[PDB]
Image: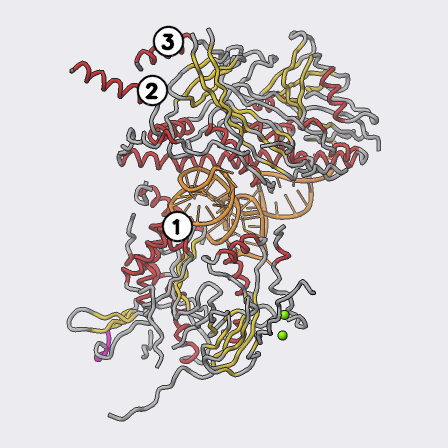
Amino acid sequence: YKTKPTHGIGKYKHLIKAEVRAINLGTDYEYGVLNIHLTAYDMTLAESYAQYVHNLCNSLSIKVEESYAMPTKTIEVLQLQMLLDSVLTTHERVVQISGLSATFAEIFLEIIQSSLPEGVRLSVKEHTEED
Amino acid sequence: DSSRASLTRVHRQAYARLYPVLLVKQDGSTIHIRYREPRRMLAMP
Amino acid sequence: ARKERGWRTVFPSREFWHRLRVIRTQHHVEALVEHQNGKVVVSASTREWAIKKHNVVACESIGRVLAQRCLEAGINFMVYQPTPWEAASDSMKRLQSAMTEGGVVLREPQRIYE
Amino acid sequence: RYRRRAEQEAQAPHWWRTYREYFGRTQQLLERKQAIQELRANVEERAARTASVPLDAVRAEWERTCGPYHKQRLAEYYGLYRDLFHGATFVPRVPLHVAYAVGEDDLMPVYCGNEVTPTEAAQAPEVTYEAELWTLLL
Amino acid sequence: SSKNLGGKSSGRRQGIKKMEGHYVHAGNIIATQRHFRWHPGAHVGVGKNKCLYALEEGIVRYTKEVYVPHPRNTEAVDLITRLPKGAVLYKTFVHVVPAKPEGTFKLVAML
Amino acid sequence: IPIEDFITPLKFLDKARERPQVELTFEETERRALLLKKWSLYKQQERKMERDTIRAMLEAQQEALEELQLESPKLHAEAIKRDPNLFPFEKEGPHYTPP
Amino acid sequence: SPWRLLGALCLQRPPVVSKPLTPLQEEMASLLQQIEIERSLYSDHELRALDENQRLAKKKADLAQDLEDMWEQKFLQFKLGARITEADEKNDRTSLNRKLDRNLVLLVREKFGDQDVWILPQAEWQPGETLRGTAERTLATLSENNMEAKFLGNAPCGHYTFKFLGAKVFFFKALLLTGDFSQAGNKGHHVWVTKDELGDYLKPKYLAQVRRFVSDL
RNA sequence: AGAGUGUAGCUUAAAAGCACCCAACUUACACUUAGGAGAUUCAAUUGACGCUCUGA
Ligand SMILES: [Mg+2]
Ligand SMILES: [Mg+2]
């Protein structure tokens, strides 16, 4: 009841939130939605790397809002000398990351570098894209 | 720590065979790749 | 004797006399027998340090032990009320089987009115 | 996790009334560890990949060790300590084995809480307990 | 002219019929509602309306208890999942503290 | 227009009779089992190591940021300021052979 | 409280060649490969080898091998660059190209009047100047080389205290993309070093604590 | 050379409960199911090895 001392013991909706810029202030800093494009030729490898990255993020108390994959680009190349075809494919997989304070980002980058797999490439940049 | 995400199995169920292909781009750098058929070498121009 | 009938919105159901509560954790597997009161009548854990000698298999063993214990106590009937995932799980199934073998029914008869 | 939390909360007392208001060595350790290791070695996992466990031995062990602990709970449940002694609990330390004769064999054993009929209990039972003086009572 | 027309519905006469402490025989309706304002607890059933009825003779009691929903009902589960790791929901319940004993042993005859 | 390459193609439907034969021994399976646990353990160890590496680094950073602040209150803010260099961060991983 | 102002830099080299796998790791890899082989559903070589072969026999009663041979020949032909340009040199501590598998770090000598300092690229920052800027300047100057030293962020890595006159030594990270070095055999004794090597060479507690924020790998 | 001490990550646990790891479901995470690994630093409440902190 309202007049009782127990009022609002059932109140739960303030415990849930049922409802982007880069804020670089002065002593407290945030990069805005960093997309980590993992480009590679093996489908498996990139995925594995992405997974690892995600896991790391989870461990480090960092949000992972989106983890989509980009389409596979069929770069059909003629091996000129006798036309020998080689239909290679490049696969891009992304892992978005929001909040990050001064000291952490560098460390994260270092970790990524340490972990980099064999024949896979990075690109860390802002969200403003068109899929 | 470069071998942590290297040991990769194909997590999909229905798929083709894959062989340890040595791919070489114009930098002069080999890469282990899973290209169609057992092509050991595929040097890129 | 009566059973608490309601609690129909809430889970789990308190309509029983005797409740089998399994507690899986890291390491060791508890398996209890309870009343409406919450009085733990008959237990079987891997922590007991007698069955810590000699996991699905472990769980099964515990269940078996409990069944014997149940018999000793004179508890022959439970309502085992698990989550769906728990029910599905192999270890739980094994435990149930063990209990059945021991001779302890996991259904429990009706109240008899009139 | 949520369920666990809820349970914990329930267990705690609170100030708003509720359901409860209206209704309710080192050496030994080392040895144990060693034993465990030995067991593991013996297994060597393969066994796990469906082993039965000897029950009688386990029972015996229980009797030796935490059987007494168990029995107190049982007694409480059955209300012996409230009725027999007006309150005030105790742990039965000495393991009592009473058995009723049925024919020549078998013997119907009296464990704590078992159903046994007056037909089987017409004659007085055999008793054993492994200890060195006492006054047995029914 | 008046664009709005229609809502001329009467009150449903819903709410608590039996307040705390009231003696209640079996089958009586304790409280009626839409959306669980109050939930059923010990010896209290539920209709199709969500109306709470007493399942034993005795005293009605109201109580703030922990809410743990059935895992098949999904919305509740989802809500629970959403919550932070120290919180518990809580909800108001209705119990019936049963008065008489289920029965007594009486002497039939001396055979 | 997001269109990924996760859909298993229509070419692989009828061509599914070439390998259904998976017939292992006891020995093989057991060996595999033995391996897996070991691998898991190794992974765990590696992750622990990684954690240690990270944590130590973090600690060092913290220490630096204490010392700096102690010895120049003007500079800590500057140090904190995230530089513009990381709009287009790029690095390829290690190859197997150099040029 | 005169705080003497010395900067520094903990320079980094990214590993070029991949690392050698452990026995267990190798085994795991093999297992994975086997599983992949098992699971998979057709190959363009396997369809055009087996079926074709079968047909040929039938015809006789009434291609792949060549391709394989060709592939083998190609493999034989294609001579690769060496993974080991480190143990074959052996005595070359001063070369950047040395350790392809591991990461690396620069390590300089400086004999002063009072002290005799075995150094990790140190600097002397000015109150008006920035720390990062100072570091950059140092990088430009003492080694005498044209470098693309990719930094990460303006925040530092590790600082260290010596007190006679209070003082400090301030370390950052920098990752070399391409370091074009002028005159290999100059008198400024510079050395490229792994983790173990770093541990070994460094006499003092000031640089012995630097190895904690180095990537161990 | 002195101070704080000393259960595996962590704890008004006393060999526990949470953290943790590999698989399989998963785009991935998450959940779930199977597995996995772990500790009283050492000698009779005292002393002697390990860290953290302050000096040289
Ligand atoms: Mg109205
Ligand atoms: Mg009206």
Q: What percent of the width, then of the height, locates residue D70?
A: 39, 65
- Assess disc 1: are there few (<14), some (14-19) or many (≥20) residues with their C-alpha within 10 Å of its C-alpha: some
Q: What percent of the width, then of the height, locates residue G35?
A: 36, 31
Q: What percent of the width, then of the height, locates residue C39?
A: 44, 69
Does the magenta run of residues contain D124? yes
Which quarter of the figure is the C terminus of chain D placed in? Answer: bottom left
Q: Amino acid at mark 1?
A: Arg
Q: Is mark 2 within 8 Å of ligand 1?
A: no
- In this picture, residue D55 sits left or right of residue E46: left
Disc 2 + disc 1, Cβ < 8 Å: no
* Residue shown at the point (60%, 42%) measured from the top left: A61
SS at badge 1: helix
Residue located beneath label 2 in the image: G45
Residue located beneath label 3 in the image: G73
Say if residue G55 shows up in the picture.
yes
Circle on res. D32: 1
Q: What percent of the width, then of the height, locates residue G27?
A: 38, 28
